[PDB]
Image: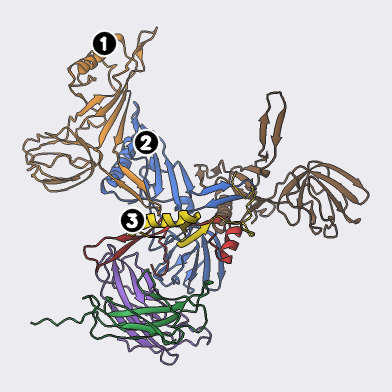
Chain colours: A blue, B orange, C brown, D purple, E green, F yellow, G red
Amino acid sequence: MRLPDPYTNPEYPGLGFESVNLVDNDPMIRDELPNGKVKEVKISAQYWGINISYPELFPDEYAFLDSRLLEYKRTGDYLDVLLPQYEAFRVRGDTKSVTIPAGQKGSQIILNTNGTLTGQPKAGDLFKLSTHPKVYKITNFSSSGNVWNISLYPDLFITTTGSEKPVFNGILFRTKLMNGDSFGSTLNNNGTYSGISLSLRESL
Amino acid sequence: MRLPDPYTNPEYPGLGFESVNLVDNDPMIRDELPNGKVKEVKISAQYWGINISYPELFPDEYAFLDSRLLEYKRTGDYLDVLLPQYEAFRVRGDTKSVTIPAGQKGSQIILNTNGTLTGQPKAGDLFKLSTHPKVYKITNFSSSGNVWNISLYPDLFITTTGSEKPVFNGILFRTKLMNGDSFGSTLNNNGTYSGISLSLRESL
Amino acid sequence: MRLPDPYTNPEYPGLGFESVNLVDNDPMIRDELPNGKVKEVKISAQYWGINISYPELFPDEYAFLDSRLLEYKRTGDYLDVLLPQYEAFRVRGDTKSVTIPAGQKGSQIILNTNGTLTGQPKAGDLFKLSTHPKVYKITNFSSSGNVWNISLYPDLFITTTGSEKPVFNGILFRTKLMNGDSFGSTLNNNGTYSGISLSLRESL
Amino acid sequence: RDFKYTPTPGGVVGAIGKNGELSWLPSLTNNVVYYSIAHSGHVNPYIVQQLENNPNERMIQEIIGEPAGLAIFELRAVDINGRRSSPVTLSVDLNSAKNLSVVSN
Amino acid sequence: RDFKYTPTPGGVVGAIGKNGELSWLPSLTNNVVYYSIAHSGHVNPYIVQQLENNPNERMIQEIIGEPAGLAIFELRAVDINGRRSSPVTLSVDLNSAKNLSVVSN
Amino acid sequence: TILDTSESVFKNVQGILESFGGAINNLSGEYRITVEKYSTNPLRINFLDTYG
Amino acid sequence: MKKILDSAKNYLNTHDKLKTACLIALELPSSSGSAATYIYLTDYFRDVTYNGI
């Protein structure tokens, strides 16, 4: 399920994201030895945290947003969040004729584009596999012919089976709405709803 | 009993919500798995919470208000409130001749108007069964002629027994006060009671 | 690896420290005797701490910056930084033909330039040995012809082996991030990432 | 179904020879998590995990460097609860010239 | 040496199905204390200690109760210093522990 | 030793060990039987290597 | 003391960020002793395959 944004629903301009906050949550056990050497240990997973802020909402905008959020809480679905700043179209073509060799469980994807894709991905972009909902950021990219060497920040959450297909454009965050236990919005005497905030967390 | 408001007592326009906060309170056993998956189990019942803020109240209006509140505290019954933003009379007609077939549990509900009601209840509006005092919130609507399919955010607390009648207008929340233990009112030199507010909470 | 900055990437002038805080962190066993005498014992190693604050970063500059930071977090190596206020090239020449006699421990150090270097390193400037990555701070200087006597605030971590070469320019701190666990960036409606800051900490 | 060993006749160096891969269509029954194939030369079985749900869509597992000679393969599907399926057996003799696919269609 | 498996047609040990037996010749290197064998699908490798008389007569270990099908047996030895021989593999198919009568009708 | 098998194997092993002050421990799956002895090759630990 | 591989010591000394994982191999009950099963678990963010398990 997609969170309402002024792409799909421009008739409600108040539903735009006044300010997004992409939080990098990678819990680690960091210990500082007296000999000056700082040591880290990583066990848990990394999850992208998204915080959405909203302006004053008119009754119709709030009605639409609240209906969507209540539909989410009713069906127990997953809110999809689209960040416009990450929607630069660089890689274009078909992602079905590209092959990803299997057995890749590290933090690096080696894929043979088979010359079917034009353009090259840029470092810091958003990358995602077609068979897993986790979202990756490209930290480095070296192309030697048709084989690409894409480096990802989160260690690969799945081991490639050889059937996965890279996804570069149209990437959505399969988030789950936090702070929904006590979710409310105050209606002022002037008819507009205020104090609406969405603390979302990537529940892959 | 009924909480006084300009609809019941028009002679006191000082009564009436300066701002109402309709919060959603669904307790949940949320657990953040190490693999990134978030698992939440719903066990405790959900309850709407209403935070009412009053404007400058003159001495007679506050006398009426706190007289009613103290009668509430004395006889110990429940305190009904009528939110006015949800009082858009979008469904005309008399709902006695509307039958809800028995044996229905969950969010979905099916009711047959038998060609009596005029008007379509859009998403975001309130809904309440005749017998049970719980107040739901319509999230999606779909009708095939006379039969109406309504999806409600909180699951039906009680399974329909075939006699419950829909209540699309004049919905009252059966609430209980949460500020009773220490409830003070300040009188200014201007002659008005300032900062009167209520933290209500739906019971059952 | 190298932290991006306008010297390495002049095309991104948004990178570059709006304000840098170079803190001194020497843990000590301080004890306040009842007679008024204060006794402190140095046991734990000292480490410089660097707090970097960035100005308004545009989306492409932040993409480059967080791509580099996520590559840091991925490959797990150290993150070198170059403080520009200490980049006053006060010592010309090539330091390969400069010998530091072996068997020297403590703050004092003696190095023979053999008539190669031009320029006097005044007090307050940085100093770093070729082999060890520790960064010192010159506190006093005294030269008798070619031989230079330099006093450093932190005692020499390793005793000179007769091959270490002085590094009076281009000194990089081998640091580790301390904000990695929860590192979020907010995007304004103006189109800039605001309040980006780093709490670095020298490792070893 | 369709446990078919698809061999690659590519001329590879003698020291390490890339044996052709093998394919087997996903099990019809849902709630299958991975696929454990026994191997002649390896005690441990190769495992391929089916996270997605793509019926009628083939899957591939490849073996490289195995010695030339007789080979026997036994593949079994595994349930999410822990059940294991019946074995699927296929024995193929490994040789560079013997590396020719079955007649198709 | 001689790491071979000979099936047992009729097998019973304490009234339970007995499969064949697998045998091998002791390593020529001295000071070997036991011969460890790894069995596919089993957490615990089968270990049988040697004997002072082993230098002459090969030892044998029996496998009982396993189902009919493929088994991968890996044999390697140890030294009192921990030194280990290179593993010896034997990929074979096993008969049922107790050949059961077919369904009457 | 007279190992009365009636008693638990735990008790018998403890009784044997208490005779010569030895100790048995299993960490990492190896059963170590060791006694308090002087060694000429200890593991060098420095206070800096230690935590604070 | 339990000695470890030389490569293990080199990796532990050289690498400061260790990505550890605990691989629980728990036994599972069954009515008859002729049936045995195991449930494998780990706290790592992704399933870990060791010895084909």
Q: Where residue A149 sits: x, y (%)?
A: 53, 67
Identify which amino acid the numbered label 2 is placed on: Leu
Q: Which of marks 1 and 2 is in front?
A: 1
Q: Residue beneath label 1, please?
A: B63
Left/right placement of residue C84 relative to residue B155 reads: right
Q: Residue beneath label 2, please?
A: A57
Left/right placement of residue C136 relative to residue C68 reads: right
Chain for numbered disc 3: F
Vertical arrangement, residue A50 with respect to residue G13, above or below: above
Q: Label for residue B11?
A: none
Spot the residue most to the front.
Answer: F2
Quarter where residue D25 is shown: bottom left
Identify which amino acid the numbered label 1 is placed on: Ala
Is residue C204 something that shows in the picture?
Answer: yes
Secondary element type, mark 3: loop
Q: Residue beneath label 3, please?
A: F7
> Decide: marks 3, 2 in contact (CB < 8 A)?
no
Identify which amino acid the numbered label 3 is placed on: Glu
Secondary element type, mark 2: loop
Secondary element type, mark 1: helix
Q: How far apart are marks 1 and 2 (CA)?
A: 35 Å
Vertical arrangement, residue A68 with respect to residue D79, above or below: above
Circle 1 crowding by C-alpha within 10 Å: few under 14, some 14–19, many from 20: few
Nearer to me, E62 or A28: E62
Circle 3 crowding by C-alpha within 10 Å: few under 14, some 14–19, many from 20: few
Quarter where residue F6 is shown: bottom left
Left/right placement of residue B175 relative to residue A110 reads: left
